[PDB]
Amino acid sequence: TTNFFIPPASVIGRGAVKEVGTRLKQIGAKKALIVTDAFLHSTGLSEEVAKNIREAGVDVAIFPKAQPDPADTQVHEGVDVFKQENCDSLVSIGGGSSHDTAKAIGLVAANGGRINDYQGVNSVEKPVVPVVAITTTAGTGSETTSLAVITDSARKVKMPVIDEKITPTVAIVDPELMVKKPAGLTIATGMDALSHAIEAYVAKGATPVTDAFAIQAMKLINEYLPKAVANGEDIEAREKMAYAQYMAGVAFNNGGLGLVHSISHQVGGVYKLQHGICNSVNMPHVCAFNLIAKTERFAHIAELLGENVAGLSTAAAAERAIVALERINKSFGIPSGYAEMGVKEEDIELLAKNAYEDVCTQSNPRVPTVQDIAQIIKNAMLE
Amino acid sequence: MTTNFFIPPASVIGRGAVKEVGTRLKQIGAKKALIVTDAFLHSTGLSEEVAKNIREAGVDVAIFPKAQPDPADTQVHEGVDVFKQENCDSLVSIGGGSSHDTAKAIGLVAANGGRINDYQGVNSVEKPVVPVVAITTTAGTGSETTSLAVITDSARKVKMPVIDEKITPTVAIVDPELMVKKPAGLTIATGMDALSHAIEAYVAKGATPVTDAFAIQAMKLINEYLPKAVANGEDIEAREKMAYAQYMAGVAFNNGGLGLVHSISHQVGGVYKLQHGICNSVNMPHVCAFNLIAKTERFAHIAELLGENVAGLSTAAAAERAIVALERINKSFGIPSGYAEMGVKEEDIELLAKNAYEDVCTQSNPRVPTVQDIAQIIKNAMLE
Amino acid sequence: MTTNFFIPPASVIGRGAVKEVGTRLKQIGAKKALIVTDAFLHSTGLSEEVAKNIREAGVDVAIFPKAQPDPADTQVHEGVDVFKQENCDSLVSIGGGSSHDTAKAIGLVAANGGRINDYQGVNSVEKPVVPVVAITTTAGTGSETTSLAVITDSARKVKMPVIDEKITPTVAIVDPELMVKKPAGLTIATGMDALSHAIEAYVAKGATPVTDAFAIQAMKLINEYLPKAVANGEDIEAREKMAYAQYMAGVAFNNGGLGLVHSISHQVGGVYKLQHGICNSVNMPHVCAFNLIAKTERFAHIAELLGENVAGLSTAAAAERAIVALERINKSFGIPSGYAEMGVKEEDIELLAKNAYEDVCTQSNPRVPTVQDIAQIIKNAMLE
Amino acid sequence: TTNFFIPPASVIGRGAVKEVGTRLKQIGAKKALIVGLSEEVAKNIREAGVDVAIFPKAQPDPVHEGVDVFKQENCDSLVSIGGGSSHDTAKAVVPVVAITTTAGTGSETTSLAIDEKITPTVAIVDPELMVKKPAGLTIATGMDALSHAIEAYVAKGATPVTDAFAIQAMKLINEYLPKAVANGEDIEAREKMAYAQYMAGVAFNNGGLGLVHSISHQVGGVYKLQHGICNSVNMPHVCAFNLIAKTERFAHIAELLGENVAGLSTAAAAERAIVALERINKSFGIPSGYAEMGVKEEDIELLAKNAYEDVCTQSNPRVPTVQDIAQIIKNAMLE
Ligand SMILES: [Mn+2]
Ligand SMILES: [Mn+2]
Ligand SMILES: [Mn+2]
Ligand SMILES: [Mn+2]
């Protein structure tokens, strides 16, 4: 008895943004709060989106106070604006920060409380405000997830908030908005997409449904991600990566992740490094730790990342996945180890301990000890 | 490019999922649900089991058990009246595609007015329809994930498709334990219709990477386990794998599209009153062979996914192997050798063919057809 | 899940194993044995040599040489009488499956009372039975290790299966040296029945990893050495290997089950008085083709274990190579081409099928049958 | 003439512990003496009309005081719960019912504590009782089971009967032992490991063991270490020593442990067996040598001597000298 949670309406493809208003009109929206970063508000994309929405008889207001690593303070600022403007819907424009902020605003405005009071897994009881998420990056997949991560203000800890009700109501994935992404950013986000697909395939809670999307995501990523890193104007590469991010997000949201994300959450937060790059640096060693758990699947992954496994044993084909991960990492210039990125040995223990406590660690195919995590990070320190 | 993906936002696929109905109904804000089912399931008690679950959870329920195979306009409007009298705020469908589609039509017409035959085709209706919770008892149809209801008009003796995004079910309940007692023939028909759904979705014109995901995985699962369920219906793992397969094929053809298999089967099964799955199974080999020039590569892939070793073959050879795979499956499941034995008359071919031309599926078929093309397909599907 | 595994606690396999009977019978602690055997065996004098071992151990002995092919209910109740008359405390069985089944049935009825027919089907006898030491002279049956006794009904002509954990022998003696003088036809019948046991247990519904182990080994050994033993009976190595394969196939089908092969041959041999292994070999390719859709992967494995090169082949193709291999072996041993040459008449088919449907084994069959399915199997095996 | 001794009744699978009393019933037992699982077991026993008593003295290593203590509370039948220790202690013909909590040892199916009358009357293998086994216990116990299967397949007294169970044990272990090491809450993995332990145990009881156990009996006795881990450390070098004896079967073992020996000579295929065992050792974190476990060179000689007189050395496919055993121990000290 497994649950499958996906946005009931998704528009994916060139020009998809042009349908925000249309989509909000079907949900029956009267007025929408747009949540974005200050920069996108300066680019004018927020204004174009608001125009489209208002054309469909849906009023709009803007909350350009989203920041990277969203915080409860701004979440509640946005709930305040929601109430003052008398909004009935939320629309998010940007990366994961915008999306998670919007989801938290909706949760608190419908069921009340502090977003602090929603840490952990929740079964909120009130009807929740619809959220329409427009993605501008090909990674994260937050337009399809039931998870928002908000940082506590006082305690400087991050809080995961999981509920089937924050699962966005409309997901708009337009590749055209992703074209001006620089090459390094494309690398980071695409490697996080690959991270999602690989972790979902070997996840403890993988269903055949999750595996469908995960496998197709690995196929599409393997072909076009280098092409999108090479020429960002290649709209076909951008479109295949858009679909790949979507499928990978659904896959990990319902199936699960693991130590890759657990480790890189701590490493990135502490050392202020990019999510995708940390994920890519530690994935080859995490998968080695996980090899005994899902051997057949890691052989399949080696084949899906583009290796000739014919005439190989399932153990050999499994290890070829690690070889492929290092091949990809070398092609996109991922750092050689964590040490280059500034990780200090004296911190590993902490990084391990906190990573042991992450919600992601529970879906990892191999049950870990704090020392297992520590040894993973140590092996990832330098090549 | 401006492609829409509609899917039930919540699905519970697993053993004992039926018990979740009320809970999920509670999470939509439902107060009074109307249960729409057939007559058998009612006599079996399932309607009242579900009803109890609903009532305990705090929701109220009424039972409309007049859904019939080959859903028809009469019962649709009748159940609409019952919906209005009992002042129900939600719908819960328990059974095969008949119950699901009839419930979709009930809620649709309950909101927006006239006869369901008026809402034929693709509709963008503007009044929100009530939530639908669909509990499936067949490893086929896919109706608990589709935005389509097949309401048959006997006034023209044709199964009419009715498509609107609002009749996409809001909760999907796929419990394999309600599918255990399915007799062998029903298992074959449902499973082969699901196979048709995946195969017609893969080669469909509007197929997208997302649809191909579910279509490929459904084909792999069907190949591995559908014979296992046909042999022993009491193997819960086989039933469960087929449940996942059917769900994914439903999503696939809902968002990618079907083709001339379903176009033809609608006419043949509406006129001669035969089972949908077996009609699909008799026509598929020939429809696919017609389509071969359109999607040679993907048909070679189907050959591999349906259990053929296409190593060292031309891509055209590997594609041809898909028809061999299909015919092998057909014989293994005892599918009638031809449409002729099923009672189809050569005289009616044209009128079936011509009418098949007007089904929406012909516009999703990979190869753009002529009425005489379809006629030749139906001719070849008569003997051997 | 929870599975019970019943096996003789002590087994002596190898040349000269018959030397240990009396020894073991003292370790178990017995004083009044009843050598149950046939009369031909009694004239061979084996009766008195085994009795010499037993009387040297210090156990009184009596001989009841009334075991016949198709062991009847009449001789069962008659031997039960002898058991009571000779105040026998222990049973020793010397012969093929007929004698073994007779001795264990004697213990059964002497314990619980009721005649033989009352114990058709699976029973859970509550009255303890006497220890049994089974000395086998045929490389088939495996009845030295089974909880089953195949006794036929007089009137209904049904070789009744009688199953109980209490009748599983306490000591099993497999001496290949007693198997040398077996004619080639008897070697064929017994060995082909052992192959039958291994195959049915591999595809049985109640198959476990333990029973699977034993079935696989039995099939490998049979493929290599049964033809060798059919050619030259004096080859003691081949006879010993066949003894091992029979032991393992007996444990496998005892604790995993059988299927329609034995269901059908029970009726055909009860009605027309025909050899068990021959009937089984005549029906096996057709039973396995029906059951293919259930265990395709395992039938491919069986093709490889019976000596087929399944390289570059689909699992469907490899599974069909199992039928090919079985037909090949049949030809190599001269098995009848069909039941028609064996005198089976189409008129009885219905009855056969009906009574086969009520056999316990049909419930072990991977593919759930109907009476008409069983009928079609028997029909297809009539001629070829 | 070869003998095959096995418990006459074995209940294997999830929930098997429910049949204890049930099986006792067909034994015709009256009371019972069990050598907080104990109380629920006794409740099920009483649920069939069977009186119960308890023997909580279950000292791990062997002893005689506990045997005589049990004798004092005399009873008609015995139930034994735990790993090898409890079974061996209750081995002291009164029926013995053996409930195993580890997927190794196989003592629930053995005639050793050395007589066929101490083979248990009933064997109960419940994977549900093994879920809470920590990863170290899982690795040790499963690797001991693999040791059993491997040693019995190349053993001198092997029969086709024993070879059946040993081959299937090796297959099941190859696929599922890493799965149970990764997530012990996987019931499929633990159930497969249960069946594999049972089969490997029957196989080594009837077919025999070899120099792996000869060496590790001494090493674990002297330095107080884990049986499975010691076996895992010397098995690569022991198998290497035995290669010339059963080269064909070692190539088969390479295949069974997940290697592709296709296109390889029987020699190369045999060497791939050592390659596979070393891979498995590294995947499970086995110590690199006995030296990291605290074994000292000065003792090797004595170890060798004592290992030579173990009966297992007579089952080894290759007949050894004390100096051969000493070389093996030395080679396994460091990597
Ligand atoms: Mn991520
Ligand atoms: Mn259909
Ligand atoms: Mn037989
Ligand atoms: Mn051991």
Image (tube, coloured by chain):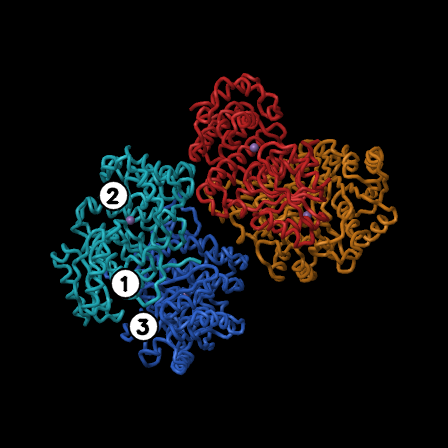
Chain colours: A cyan, B blue, C orange, D red
**What distance separates the C-alpha of mark 3 from that of mark 2?**
56 Å
- Find numbered disc 2 in the image and state the secondary structure of the residue it sits on: helix
Q: Identify the residue under disc 1.
A: A108
Image quadrant where residue D118 sits: top right
User: Which chain is indicated by disc 3?
Assistant: B
Residue B205 shows up from this direction = no
Q: Nearer the viewer, mark 3 or mark 2?
A: 2
Indicate yes or no: mark 3 CB to ligand 2 under 8 Å: no
- Find numbered disc 1 in the image and state the secondary structure of the residue it sits on: helix
Indicate yes or no: mark 2 CB to ligand 1 under 8 Å: no
**What distance separates the C-alpha of mark 3 from that of mark 1?**
41 Å
**Residue B382: where, in percent of width, then height?**
45, 65
Which sits in the foreground, D311 or B262? D311
Q: Is residue B87 left or right of residue A103?
A: right
Total labels drawn: 3
Image quadrant where residue A380 sits: top left
B243 relative to A335, above or below: below
Residue kind at label 1, given as amino acid type: Val
**What distance separates the C-alpha of mark 1 from that of mark 2?**
28 Å
Q: Identify the residue under disc 2.
A: A270
- Find numbered disc 3 in the image and state the secondary structure of the residue it sits on: strand
B162 relative to B306, above or below: below
Q: Residues within 10 Å of mark 3 (few under 14, many from 20)?
A: some
User: Which chain is indicated by disc 2?
Assistant: A
Checking the image for residue B121, the label placed there is: 3
Residue kind at label 3, given as amino acid type: Gly
Q: Residues within 10 Å of mark 1 (few under 14, many from 20)?
A: many
